[PDB]
Image (cartoon, rainbow, N blue to C red):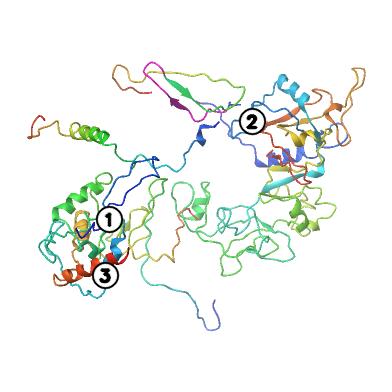
Amino acid sequence: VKAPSVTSLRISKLSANQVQVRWDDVGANFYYFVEIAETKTNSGENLP
Amino acid sequence: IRDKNNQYFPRLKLAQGRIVRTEIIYDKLTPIIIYDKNIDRNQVKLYVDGA
Amino acid sequence: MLFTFFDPIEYAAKTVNKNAPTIPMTDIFRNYKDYFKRALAGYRLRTYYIKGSPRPEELANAIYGNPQLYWVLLMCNDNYDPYYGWITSQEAAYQASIQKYKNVGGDQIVYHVNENGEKFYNLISYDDNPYVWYDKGDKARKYPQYEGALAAVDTYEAAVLENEKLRQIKIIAKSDINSFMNDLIRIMEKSY
Amino acid sequence: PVNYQLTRTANAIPEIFVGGTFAEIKQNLIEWLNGQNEFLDYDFEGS
Amino acid sequence: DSSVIYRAIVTSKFRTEKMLNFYNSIGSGPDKNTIFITFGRSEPWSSNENEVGFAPPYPTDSVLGVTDMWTHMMGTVKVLPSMLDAVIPRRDWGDTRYPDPYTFRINDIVVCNSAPYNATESGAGWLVYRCLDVPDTGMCSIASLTDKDECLKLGGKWTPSARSMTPPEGRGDAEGTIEPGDGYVWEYLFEIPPDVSINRCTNEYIVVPWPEELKEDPTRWGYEDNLTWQQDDFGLIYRVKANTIRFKAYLDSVYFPEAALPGNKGFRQISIITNPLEAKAHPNDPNVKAEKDYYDPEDLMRHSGEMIYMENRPPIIMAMDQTEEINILFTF
């Protein structure tokens, strides 16, 4: 019974040391946990 | 049909010019847009879907 | 000064950024092209100059007119684009060819030109095969077109073929232009 | 609103037209003139 | 992997029986389930309700999610078997408001005779036809192939590239062929009386009769004449491969004791429970199974019976007009 996937995931007012994320409500009683990752490694480009 | 001494009487309609297909493929971005300006926009059948 | 001739008006631009500053501007909104059209009545039979030279945009200072008028040549052909409207240097079209197709397809073959001039458009031969042409799709064949034979115009030739047909223009004959322009004003002062 | 997909916009002149404040034009031209293209070989002068 | 391997698939006919099992399961005596519809949830949730989107609290099946429900239930209605009906997807022949009006796959049931643009017989009846074959032209289904028959072997679904002129005209199987003209071989299957179609059939679905109402007359359903190698083949609910059922009730039938509350504040969540016990004063009483017609939910025992379905929806305030309709169409 997959919980409804979040929708309309946007970033707003990002700074160098601060970034904010926003997404639609998707439900009253659910919870949301997040994941953050570097991509470029020391000025490289790497595969997912 | 066939009647009496064997004969057929097709009443078929008719039009001038050639006929052409130019199938290609559909996508959600590039519009079809055929080119030659001699097209008769009255008589066309686009079916393309298998129907 | 056969353009202008009226006033700057003022261009409010208030529909965007309310309380925008008014900037006096040469007045290009009169529907000039109509004045020319109605005034021209009676001066017609302006002959066909055929051009003949990749005259830069202004031949006005050579042929009829010549106060470097740079138009009455425009209003002739009802030119929508003052740049690519007139014919261009032969190389320009070639130069224009690349930027057109540079993004996609590279150089191509636009149509195969039967003799008597029947264009085809995405019709393709098979060499080392039957000599009959096929569309660029339905690769199963089964649906041939134009059992005959013809010759493709590729791309460069087309642009040449397309812009080169753009050389004919009206003139007003270098005779009327003074008498003509003497009318063309009168209609203008008329409506105000 | 609630769902962010409802934002849209009213009648909006896109950023394509708008039009210059002057000096911002000076900025964009310099970046297009000096950069990405020439790295000046210009024969006029430093100024 | 080297082992014995067996490749098995349940047949679609299994479903329609399962559907036929849910029907007949409604009755007064024991071993016959009794279904109720419940509304309740008078109090609004949050303040973002009444806005656009925003979603409701997603309902959970736990014991906590059931307990509160019974506290908020505003009213209930008992589903009688009469107001339940079989349904199938309807494709009206030659209607332009739905895809492929003039073309048809190998076997697709298609109703004709309703609305003028299809005529066929008169005296109404809303005739229905299975379509056993198609003209052969046009590329279809898997890969390329070419011809129909070879596309019919190796699986495949062939779409005719030729519009089928005129609706099926006859009363008996394979009405095509038998004439140089085109068309393909539709197969009559039953009929829909005009009286039922104005009530029981919506424009999304056409009713197909339970193998009961076909008795106490067949004729009303235009099934009075049939090949029938068997004495009956009476139920045709299998012939159509009817996969689904449809419920209908007027909200005037549901019982709200308060009668001013559901109107002022809407019922925000609907759930259907099975086999509730009657109100017991104390656990001094024997267990009885709910009967009669209305049941103010006060008279239902808490957690009395099991609930197959919960819905949570924004307020859906209801007017008191004698027509508004429940739907709740089951896909069994």
Chain bearing tag 1 is C
Which SS class for mark 2?
Answer: loop
Pick the residue in front: E286 or C57. C57
Amino acid type of the residue that numbered disc 3 sits on in the rendered structure: Ala
Which SS class for mark 1?
Answer: loop
Which range is magenta? A4-18
Q: Which residue has dot 1 on it?
A: C126
Residue A10 lies in the magenta stretch:
yes
Task: Confirm whether residue B50 shows in the render.
Answer: yes
Above or below — where is E44 with respect to C169?
above
Amino acid type of the residue that numbered disc 2 sits on in the rendered structure: Glu
Q: Residue at x 37, y 62 (%)?
A: B20
Q: Residue at x 26, y 57 (%)?
A: C6
Pick the residue in front: C12 or E76. C12
Mark 3–mark 2 CB contact (< 8 Å): no
Which SS class for mark 3?
Answer: helix
Chain bearing tag 3 is C
Where is residue E304 shown, x and y percent of the image?
Answer: 82, 24
Amino acid type of the residue that numbered disc 1 sits on in the rendered structure: Tyr
Query: Disc 3 and disc 1: Cα gap in Å?
Result: 58 Å
Pick the residue in front: C10 or D10. C10
Disc 3 vs disc 1: which is toward the camera?
3
Where is residue A46 shown, x and y percent of the image?
Answer: 33, 22
Q: Residue at x 55, y 81 (%)?
A: B3
Residue C118 lies in the magenta stretch:
no
Question: Residue E9 has which mark?
Answer: none
